[PDB]
Every structure is written in structure tokens, then in C-alpha cells.
Amino acid sequence: SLTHRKFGGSGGSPFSGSGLSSIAVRSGSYLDAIIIDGVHHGGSGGNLSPTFTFGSGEYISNMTIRSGDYIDNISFETNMGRRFGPYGGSGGSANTLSNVKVIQINGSAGDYLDSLDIYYEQY
């Protein structure tokens, strides 16, 4: 009983994330890129965060995304209580996925990370 939900603007070219084994971001005041299993989606500006590597049986359970035209900020927490972020700036509007199991992260990107389309189960 999966759902997909989009965050962010209408720009960029679509991508599918290659798995959810690791995540990093390149960020400044925007999310310049999300890095999924070492592959970036977005541009080259901003600073490279350390990589969050998921443990066995670990998945994103809560996520807060700030966005406007672009993804502005990402933070998440896993089912095991580990946290990533926040990374990015304070613009846009905040939306949260709570008590979920994220299965796949897709989106659209150009010079920035325009949008995310998150596939998840809802509890």
C-alpha cells in the first residue's frame, strides 16, 4: 500500500535513486544535490556532507523537507533513531513525512535539486 509524494518545484530533469544504502547532500542555502549511493542529483555548488550509510534493516522513518522552487533543507530520522541533517537553508515551506518506511527516493534536478518524489509506506 505504497504512496509517492512530491516536494519541491517544477524544474529539472527526472531521476530515480539507485538504492537507499547511503545518502549525502551538497548544500548551502539550497540543496544543490542529493547524493544517493554515491551518485549526485543536482549541481556542483555547495559543501559535501559526510555520507550516512544505512545499517541492515535500517530505513527512513521520519523526514522533514523545506522546499520552494528547489529543495531547501533535508533532515531525517531512521527506524533505529539515527539522524541526518538538517542540511540546507531556512526558505520555502516545511513538510514532514512521519511514521513512514521510505523505500525509494526519486526527484528532478538541474543546477539544484528541484524536487523529490518519495515512495513510502505509511503507519
Image: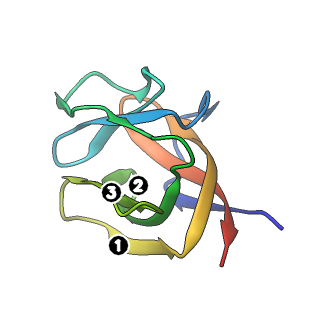
Q: Nearer the viewer, residue 5 or 8?
A: 5
Q: Residues within 10 Å of mark 1 (few under 14, many from 20)?
A: some
Q: Position of residue 54 (x, y in %)?
A: 44, 40
Task: State the separation of the CA atoms marked 3 and 2.
Answer: 29 Å
Amino acid under disc 1: Ser
Reading the chain from its start, which is encountered first: label 1 or label 2?
A: 2
Image quadrant where residue 104 sits: top right
Q: Nearer the viewer, mark 1 or mark 3?
A: 3
Q: Judge whether residue 94 can be spotted in this image.
A: yes
Residue visible at 16% across and 42% down in the picture: 28
Q: Nearer the viewer, mark 1 or mark 2?
A: 1
Task: State the separation of the CA atoms marked 1 and 2.
Answer: 10 Å
Image quadrant where residue 18 sits: top right
- The residue beneath circle 2 is 69
Q: Nearer the viewer, residue 25 or 46?
A: 25
Q: Judge whether residue 33 can be spotted in this image.
A: no
Q: How many marks?
A: 3
- Mark 3–mark 2 contact, CB under 8 Å? no
Q: Position of residue 15 (x, y in %)?
A: 62, 32
Reading the chain from its start, which is encountered first: label 1 or label 3?
A: 3
Residue visible at 24% across and 53% down in the picture: 85
Task: State the separation of the CA atoms marked 1 and 3.
Answer: 24 Å
- The residue beneath circle 3 is 82
Amino acid under disc 2: Asp
The secondary element bearing badge 2 is classed as loop
Residue visible at 84% across and 68% down in the picture: 1
- The residue beneath circle 1 is 93
Q: Position of residue 30 (x, y in %)?
A: 25, 47
